[PDB]
Image 1 (spheres, rainbow, N blue to C red):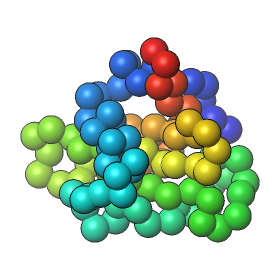
Image 2: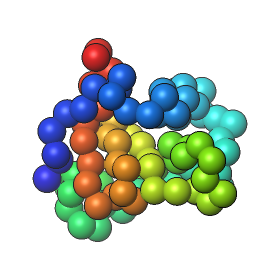
Image 3: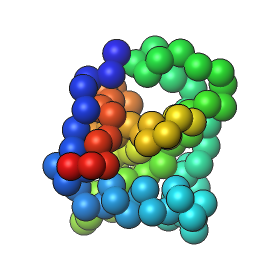
Length: 96
């Protein structure tokens, strides 16, 4: 279950960077950017394998890849933010 809908402005500014790179299909900072997200925990609505892809939201000052991601779905503006390695997701409202 998707935990509501968070304003893009309430997310780290790096989330906007990730959205830009999704739109340009890169170049991406991490090797796992663009891989299929399996949604094994049924947090997001069930869809075909390959419906969802995952991308890093860089954590500033982090040595590693951290816990922040955007998962894309296929539908118009269908993008989800997680700040905890997929444990929970919010829909990203790019209008606020």
